[PDB]
Amino acid sequence: HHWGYGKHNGPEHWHKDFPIAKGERQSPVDIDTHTAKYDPSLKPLSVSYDQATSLRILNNGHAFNVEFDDSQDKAVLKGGPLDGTYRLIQFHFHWGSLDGQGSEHTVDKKKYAAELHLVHWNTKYGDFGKAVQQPDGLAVLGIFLKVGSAKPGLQKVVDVLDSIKTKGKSADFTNFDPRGLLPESLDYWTYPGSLTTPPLLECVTWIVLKEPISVSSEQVLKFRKLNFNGEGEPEELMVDNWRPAQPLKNRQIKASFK
Ligand SMILES: Cc1cc(C)c(S(N)(=O)=O)c(C)c1
Ligand SMILES: OCCN1CCNCC1
Ligand SMILES: [Zn+2]
Image (cartoon, rainbow, N blue to C red; front, side):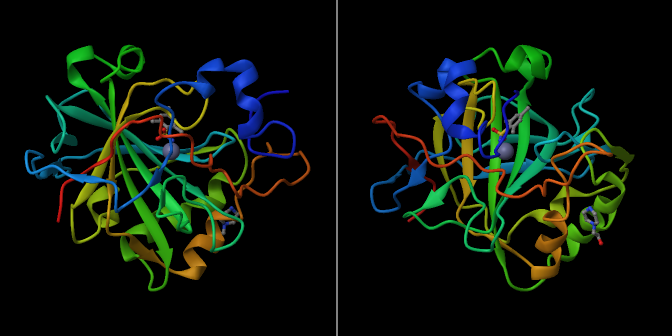
């Protein structure tokens, strides 16, 4: 009876196994754009993905992960609200059963169709497993997806999904460039938070881009053909794998703009 999103093991149950679910810096949150404080001291975000080395794609039974070789200083996030250098380890998405829901963060209560998370760990802690034990261990770049025109740079991901339909499937996934998933603007909001799935560790500096990317209806329909179940189990479509907004608890969300 492991955690998931389904009828009896979803977000409102997670606190029983992971009491930090009711902690002081949980994610995601609603971003109240009017109460976000412009911080002129924030720097432009530096996203250096030129040398990124994707390796594999994995259906982990919750989402799919596109995984990167993080054994050298390649694909790094720095600047913005960050001290130091954070290395890309994986990205994944959260999405809905319908275009009207799917994102984890909300903007003035608006839900997007989906949300991309590019997960990075602080190089001062040596790898990912040690970084998640620290309050400044991770930096996650969050990008909203709306349904409209296709995102050409997403199509290589969409096309491999049928090879990883079910939980625990993987496929070689080399030479994928995550720069093709980024919007024009790197304007962002930022706040201290957590993983959004168990173990819900309070180790993340969240950086949420204001400008969404557009994906097509056909691209997101393909995400909704994935399965939460393993091969040879009854089909449970992988949809609505998002945690709802959690209490802000007096944390301040800062804006890089306006
Ligand atoms: C391992 C892992 C899993 C997940 C779902 C996340 S998240 N959703 O971006 O907070 C992170 C940071 C790290
Ligand atoms: O054309 C791609 C459709 N696939 C089929 C099964 N897994 C999800 C996406
Ligand atoms: Zn996520």
